[PDB]
Image (tube, rainbow, N blue to C red):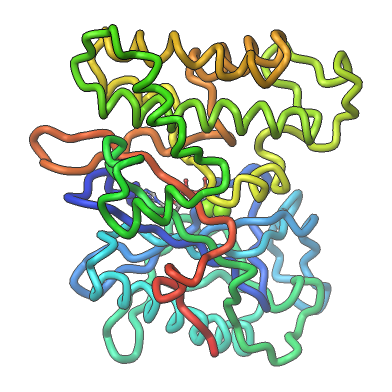
Length: 356
Ligand SMILES: Nc1ncnc2c1ncn2[C@@H]1O[C@H](COP(=O)(O)OP(=O)(O)O)[C@@H](O)[C@H]1O
Ligand SMILES: [Mg+2]
Ligand SMILES: [Mg+2]
């Protein structure tokens, strides 16, 4: 079994995703995403081997007929998914990039001498890296996995196949305290002006933590307003809101549609309703009560009520979120909130492996 991601980090964390070019993985239909993982010889889990984009049904080449059953098998692109590490842990970041580049060279040899065969659990030649196979019911095949033989491909990685995910303490979003926080706050959907706006609305209120409440308000309102903007732009069905009732033609498959995710640029990966937990019951009530009018002064009553209710009931920004991540003291953990960079910006390029 592939180990689950560690959930706790002392400070800000980073994970990477890297879709490979030059090969596919074929597995039985409805297989689990993870088929293996690469770890250091010391035992530290570095990245997972996963199936990513479905490339169609697998057809075992006739010249490679082996008496085996490949019925209903699907081909997918391979994505290398790192185990998160601390953002300032240079050695952990470097070992992940190096282990990914090593596995690409091992894949290049595998499609040359063992095309349409499963990867074997081996140790690298220098002894640095170890492959562990968790699902042996797979095959690795060059190109799109149609031909028995490769076109002598070198297995590569490129920025268009790359993403980075950053995890920060929820209480830090809006403080601009670290370079990571400042990069996250530069997200086009985040409206820092909502912090000072909240303070103006709540002068008569005796709030337990005014600065924290203003930060949470700005973060949540920015997400709710962006969701409403996107639902209108792309014609997305949110809860009971119907875009056709506002003469908007549906132009996306939902919140999880890749073009909707891309429109966020910096995609929230944590369930918005979790942040309410970093506040007192009283402060959370004050924050939540003030969000509704921010939507209603910009969007129709139906869109506003539906977006507000969707997130209130634990609605996700774009599918299953990373909601169990924590930061700070191991004994008293604080909520970490995660963000996916759809395109890796210049500031995070050094975290990604490069073939060239
Ligand atoms: N605590 C964390 N801090 C930072 N990045 C994390 C953390 N936990 C997971 N990630 C990263 O989240 C990314 C996507 O994770 P995952 O949920 O497995 O992908 P998917 O939803 O596409 O199946 C990976 O780059 C991974 O390293
Ligand atoms: Mg992934
Ligand atoms: Mg991604």
